[PDB]
Length: 103
Length: 72
Image (cartoon, rainbow over all chains, first blue to last red):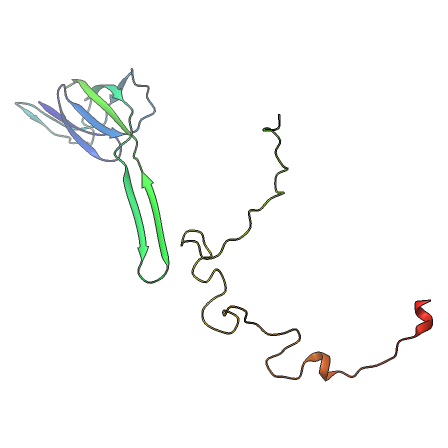
């Protein structure tokens, strides 16, 4: 009982009632979001996508958090050429919990 | 209010400091390049030097004279 859907350019396989982290979305932390772009739905019986994105499959998900990822330190260094550079990055992420998976 | 006065924008530049790190830009000789006479401490050529060629103020002939009546 799991489904495959495309959210932020990268596909996720999520089972019922589990939390999945995906790219930042323009949704407030206390609102449900829709994912009608369901790549595949799996159950005891198997249903595939003759046309991409099934026919009526949707996924109900609730936003939980809108935090930032772990800091990543970017170092660029040229050997013997008197060039050093430092940078930091924290990627924005959105935690969402899957509430319901349709057929 | 003595701790609220500020100068006009662009009045100060903070100057250039040489040889203080890589990220500061002009470090490691502070913008005077690699070896050479100009890179040395106190190096350089005097005014009018052309590297040995006859200077312009020597190739040309002196002309005229100064009139004392012009100053009065």
